[PDB]
Amino acid sequence: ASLSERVDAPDVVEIPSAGADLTWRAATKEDIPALFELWRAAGAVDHPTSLVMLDELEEEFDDDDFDPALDSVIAVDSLGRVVAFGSATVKSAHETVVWVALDGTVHPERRGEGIGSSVLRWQEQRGLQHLAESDECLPGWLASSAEEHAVWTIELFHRNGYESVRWWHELERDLAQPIPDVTLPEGIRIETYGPEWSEPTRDAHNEAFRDHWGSQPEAREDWEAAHRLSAFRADLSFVAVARDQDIVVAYLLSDVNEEEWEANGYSFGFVDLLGVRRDWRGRKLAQALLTHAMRAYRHEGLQRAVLDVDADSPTGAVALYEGLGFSLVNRSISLIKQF
Ligand SMILES: CC(=O)SCCNC(=O)CCNC(=O)[C@H](O)C(C)(C)COP(=O)(O)OP(=O)(O)OC[C@H]1O[C@@H](n2cnc3c(N)ncnc32)[C@H](O)[C@@H]1OP(=O)(O)O
Ligand SMILES: NC(=O)C1=CN([C@@H]2O[C@H](COP(=O)(O)OP(=O)(O)OC[C@H]3O[C@@H](n4cnc5c(N)ncnc54)[C@H](OP(=O)(O)O)[C@@H]3O)[C@@H](O)[C@H]2O)C=CC1
Image (cartoon, rainbow, N blue to C red; front, side, top):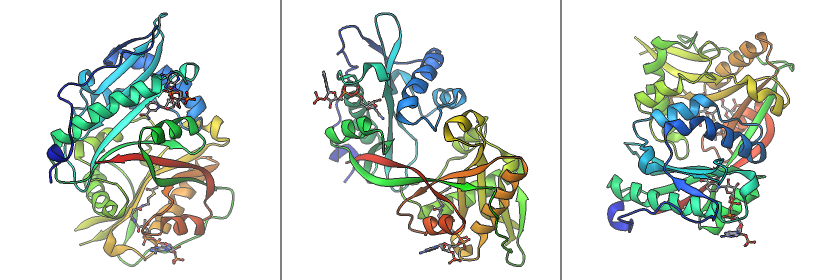
């Protein structure tokens, strides 16, 4: 049955009103600098090793899938300080799940007074509208996440009926320790990523991540947007290329965010995406790309490689990273309510 029939979505969503010194409204792009400061204040408590970047907020507000008039709320105190924000955002196409991202936060100094509950209550009402409006016969997931230490976020989500449904491990690899050498199958070469590989790599990724939990295919616009972020490092990203005519059979995309080095305790490159096409797996291509990237990171003087992995990876990514010397740093949790 359709989500528009399974979900009883409100005809009208009420912006919050609670907080005697608070004024609430939808956010606009003009709020981005104050939101940056909010996210940084909150992240110092909730996720100090990961920094929200200004250009991420800019791309989010510029995304055609995001209507800030209907998909965002912001709370301002009596001195005009921004103290909370929430959004509820859905993409335009869905493959196996209708994913609604419920992103928001409350300033650490204004927690424990019901402001988070107000934000999540609003996010869920708008989220139900996103689900019904999708008119899809797929699971509907209203979703957020938290680092395991952020019990204040986790407990708010559990209190509201969201469940911990998936676990993520951040892993690090010391680039000063020996990096193994791995050979490629015949007919395969490694190239540095660049614009000419964008579409072949998007195609490879969308196939490979059919086997990753939750993932939906990446539309071209969103793919290209993520590559405009200052953190993306095309020259530390690599593809393995075979002949079918060339095709990308494995790929590894990297970020470098030097503003995160201090809190993480080392300089590091971040493995953002790593995939191998189904028919080319079990041939060491992931190892070949990871080791190639680790040598590239080391040559630039970076101390570590860092990445995230589904703790229950169905294609064995955990064993892959463990065998290459990655070790646990931190854990995070997907918090989801299903319709
Ligand atoms: C940073 C991120 O993006 S995290 C998400 C990781 N990417 C994905 O999940 C995408 C979907 N999966 C894939 O693309 C592929 O299956 C990958 C990337 C996990 C691995 O692809 P491959 O090229 O076949 O990896 P590779 O051949 O180099 O290494 C295989 C290793 O996996 C490990 N492994 C353990 N159990 C399994 C399993 N059940 N199935 C597969 N691999 C397993 C082993 O350590 C194995 O090494 P071995 O040679 O000693 O046996
Ligand atoms: N990712 C997301 O989408 C969102 C994330 N968050 C995050 O969740 C975490 C919690 O936010 P926070 O503002 O503290 O949540 P709340 O203050 O709303 O709730 C947290 C605790 O405070 C108490 N409380 C609840 N309602 C009231 C109220 N009306 N008046 C007084 N006390 C109340 C309750 O504890 P008790 O039973 O003891 O009274 C509750 O368990 C933060 O880290 C925040 O950033 C919040 C919203 C959205």
